[PDB]
Image (cartoon, coloured by chain):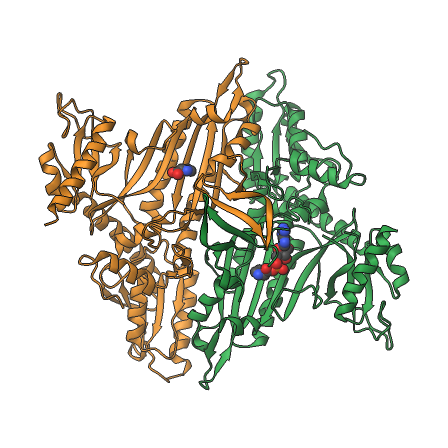
Chain colours: A orange, B green
Amino acid sequence: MVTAKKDENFSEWYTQAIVRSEMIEYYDISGCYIMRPWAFHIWEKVQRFFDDEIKKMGVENSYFPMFVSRHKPEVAWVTHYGDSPLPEKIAIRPTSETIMYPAYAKWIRSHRDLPLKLNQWCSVVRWEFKQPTPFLRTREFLWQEGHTAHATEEEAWELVLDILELYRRWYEECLAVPVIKGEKSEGEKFAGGKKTTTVEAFIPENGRGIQAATSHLLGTNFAKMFEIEFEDEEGHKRLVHQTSWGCTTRSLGVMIMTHGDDKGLVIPPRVASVQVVIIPILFKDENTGEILGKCRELKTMLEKADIRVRIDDRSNYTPGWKYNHWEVKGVPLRLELGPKDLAKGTARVVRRDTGEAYQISWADLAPKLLELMEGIQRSLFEKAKARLHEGIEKISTFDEVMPALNRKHLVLAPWCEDPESEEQIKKETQKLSEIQAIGAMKTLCIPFDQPPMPEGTKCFYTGKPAKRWTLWGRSY
Amino acid sequence: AMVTAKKDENFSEWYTQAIVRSEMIEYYDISGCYIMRPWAFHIWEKVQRFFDDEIKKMGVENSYFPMFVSRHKLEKSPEVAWVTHYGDSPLPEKIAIRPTSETIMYPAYAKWIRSHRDLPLKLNQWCSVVRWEKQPTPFLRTREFLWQEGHTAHATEEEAWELVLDILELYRRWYEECLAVPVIKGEKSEGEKFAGGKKTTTVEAFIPENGRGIQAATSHLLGTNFAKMFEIEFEDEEGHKRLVHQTSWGCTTRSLGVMIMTHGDDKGLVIPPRVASVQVVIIPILFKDENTGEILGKCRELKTMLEKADIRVRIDDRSNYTPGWKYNHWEVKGVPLRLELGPKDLAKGTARVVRRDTGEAYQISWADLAPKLLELMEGIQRSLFEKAKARLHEGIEKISTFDEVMPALNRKHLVLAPWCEDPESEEQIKKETQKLSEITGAMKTLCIPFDQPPMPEGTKCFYTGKPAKRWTLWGRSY
Ligand SMILES: Nc1ncnc2c1ncn2[C@@H]1O[C@H](COP(=O)(O)OC(=O)[C@@H]2CCCN2)[C@@H](O)[C@H]1O
Ligand code: PRO
C-alpha cells in the first residue's frame, strides 16, 4: 500500500509506487534497476508499435558492438579478461555515432546508396548520474536510436518530422501522455546538428518539464567530420544530410507520473500486461471448483476477444488484500466474482481510474470490457491534456515569470531567441529562487504551434524585438 | 559483388565472401566483434519472433536485468570482461560485464519466491553478452553476441526437467523447422556441461566441409545447486521449506552462422523461405522504353495478390541498376524465389520464376501465382532440410574400437562410439587425438544422443575397454 500522497510528497510517492507495483527490483550496483515483467511488458508494447511504424518507413534494424578502441576520454575501460590483462584496453562506447559513422562512410559511395536508414534497439550505459531514480536518472536504460543519411536536406527534414510524429503517437496513443512538439533553442540542441526537434511533457506535481524524445536534423557537419561522401548523378562529391532520433525507458517514468494517484499506478490498457484481473471471492479454504471454474470459463471467453487476463487465485490472501495489490499495480479493470455473483449470473467490474463499479451479465462481459477499456484510455488522455493546458501561463513580461514558476506552471513568452539571454535568464531565475529561501528556468521548446505574434512585440526579457513564442520552465 | 571462392575448396574464404558480399557482416577494429547489418538482422528477427511467441505460450515473461555484475555476486572466471577504470581513475570496486545472468537474477529470485504459490517463476531475457575467448568466427564464435537466456524455478525436479525438454524441443524447431538445419538432441558429458548445474541437454549441428560439430543451443537442469548458493527457498503446503528446482536455457546468433554454412553454395546465401524477409523479389525488366509504365503496374498488382496470401514480396523497381545486376544482387543475398516480368511476359498472362536453391525456372499464370509459389516455397524449405539431413547422416561413422577413430576423423567425420563415461577418459581421449592429429585437432564429446542405438551385452568402451554405458557422439568441434 502507498502511504505518501502524490501531491504532498511526490518523490516519496514515486518511489513507493514503482516498488509496491512490482515494476522494478533493486540491485547491488548503484544506479541499476531490474525491470520486472509488469514494466517490461509496457516497453515491449511501445517497442512493437514504434518498430512497426519505422519499418513501414524503410528503416531496418541493426546491431553494432558495444566496444570501441583507443582510436576514439571519460569513458569506461575494460582492461582484463579473467585475471589476464588485455593487449590494449578497450572502452565501452559512449556514443553510437563513433562506431556507425565510419561504417556509413564505407557503405555510401554513390547516390544509388541513399537513403540509408538504420535503427538499433539496445541498452545504454551512462556513468555520471547524480541521484538515481528508476526510469528517470539511471546508470543503464533501454532505448532505440535511429540514424539516417539522405541526398538532400529536405528529405532528411521530412524524415525528422515523420519520426517526431511517431513519438507523439508513442506517447499519446500508447501511453496516453499528451506532448508538445517543438524546436529546441540553440543552447539546448544537439552539439553538432542543425536543428533538434523534441516532444515535451509536463509534470504538474512539481511543475517540471521533461523531454519525452528527440529527433535531430544533423545536417552535414558529421558527414564533413567523418568523410561520409557520395558522388551525385553529375559526378560531383557531396556530403550526406543526416538525422538521428532516440527514445528511452524514461517514457515509462513519464507515464507513471502522469496517471498515478494516491492509491498508486494507473497503467493505460493499451500497454498494461494484464488488462483485467479476475479475483475470486474466496477466503482461506473454500476450495470447490464452483468459483474457480466459472473464473476459468470467463478468462477463456475474454481472451478470445483478445483481452489480457489473469486470475489471482492465491489462497493465502484476502479479497481486500488482492484488491489493494492490483490497485497499486494499476490494472485498469478488476472483475470480482463471488458466491452472490455466481448466484445471479453476473460479475462486478471496477475501473481503476475512477473507481466506478458495474454489474455485468456474463454474456455482456467481453463487449462491455472492450468498451470500458477504450473509455479508460481516452479518459486518461483527456484529463492529462486538460492538466497540461492548465499548467501553461501565457506571459508578456519578466515580472510574470517568478509568480508562474511558483504556481508550478510553465510559461509561454515572446522571445528574441538570442543564446546569451537564455543563460542570463537561467542565472537570474536560479538566484531569485535562492533568495526566496527564507531552481533555474530554461527553454523547453519553441512550439511548432505558434500563436500570432503582433507586430513589434518585445521579448519578455531583453526588450529587443521578439521572434517567436517560447516555452519555459523548471525542468528535469 | 558476387562470390568467387568455392565452398568445397577454401571454406574460410568462401564463408567470409558469402557473409560480406550479402551485406550481412561488416568487419570491425576489435577482434571478435562484428557489425550485424540489416540483412542478417532480418533473419535474427524472424527466429526471435518464433521463439518468443512459443515461450509466451508456455507462460514465460520477458524482463531486463542489468548488464553489470559485482565481484562478490559473480564469485559466490577466465572469460569475464572487467571494467576497472573510468577515465584514468580506477573504480573503487571493479565490476564485470554479463557473461550470463544466473548471478544477476538469482538474488532477485531468492527475494521474490516465498511460497509454493510463487511457482513456477518463468522469466526470459533478450540481450547481448560478452565472453572473451580461441580465434573468432563471425556468428559462430564472437566475443559479444546476441541471445536469449531463460531462467525458471519450480517446486519439483520433474517439472523442471519437463521444462528443460520442452525448451530443447523448441530449439529443435528453431533450427529444423525454421532454419532447415538438422540437429541431434543429447546430454552433455559431465565435463562438457554447464558449470554448477546438474544436467545439460543440447542440440548439436555439423559442418561437413571441415568435419566440425557445433553446439547449436542448450537447456540446463540446474537442479537445486544454485538454489543452495543463493538461498532460493519456498514453503510447501505442509509448511516445510524446500529448495526450488531451476532450469536455464539459451540460444544465440550462432544459429545464423550455421544456417549460412549449411545452405550456402558457390553463388552465396540460400535463405530458407520460413526466415526469409523477402521470399519473392519481383524484377521488372525495362529496356528501350518498351512498356515501362504498364509493366510496373502489373508488378504492383502481383505484389498485392501475393501479399493477400502472406507471401513477403519486394519489388526492385530501383531505376539505377540493370536487371542483370538485380539478379546477381538478390541471388548473393539468397532470396529463395525470383519473379521476372518483362513485356514478353505481360503479353502472355504469365511470369517467369526462378528458385534460388536449384536454379529451376517456371512459367506461371498470374491466376496460379499465389498457390504455386506457396508450393515451391514449401518445397524449397523441405529440400534444404532433407539435403542437409542426408549430409548429416553420411557425416557420422559408428565405430567400436579406438583404431577406427583417426581414419574417421580424417574423412572429416563424427564418430558414434560406445563409451564408459569416465570423466578422466574424456581428457585422455582429447590429448591422444590431438597428438595423433599432428602426425584444434582434438576430438571431444559433442553429445550423448537421446536416440540411443542398441547396446549388445558386453560391449566394451571404445577407449578404456571397461563396459560401455552409452553410445556417445564425438567429433572435432568449434
Ligand atoms: N562465442 C560465442 N559466440 C556465439 N554463440 C555462442 C558463443 N558461446 C556460446 N554460444 C552459444 O550460446 C549458448 C550459450 O550457452 P551456455 O552453455 O554458455 O549456457 C548458459 O550460459 C546458460 C543458458 C542461458 C543462461 N545460462 C550456447 O548454446 C551456444 O549456442
Ligand atoms: O543523444 C541523442 O539525443 C541522440 C539521439 C540519437 C542518438 N543520439
- B350 left or right of B265? left
- B199 left or right of A178? right
Q: Residue furthest right?
A: B403
Q: Is residue A137 above or below residue B421?
A: above
Quadrant of the rendered image containing residue A395: top left
| Residue B53 x %, y % | 52, 57
Q: Is residue A137 above or below residue B194?
A: above
On-image quarter of the N terminus of chain A = bottom left
Quadrant of the rendered image containing residue A291: bottom left
Q: Is residue B174 visible?
A: no
| Residue B345 x %, y % | 65, 27
| Residue B348 x %, y % | 66, 28
On-image quarter of the C terminus of chain A = top left
Front-lying residue, A177 or B404: B404
Front-lying residue, B371 or A396: A396
**Count of numbered circles in the view:** 0
The residue at 68%/60% (across/down) is B203
Q: Is residue B26 visible?
A: yes
Q: Is residue B288 above or below residue A99?
A: above
- A35 left or right of A361? right
Front-lying residue, A33 or B273: A33
Front-lying residue, A323 or B257: B257
Q: Residue furthest bottom?
A: B238
Instruction: Answer with the quadrant where ligand 1 appears in the image.
Output: bottom right
| Residue A218 x %, y % | 40, 29
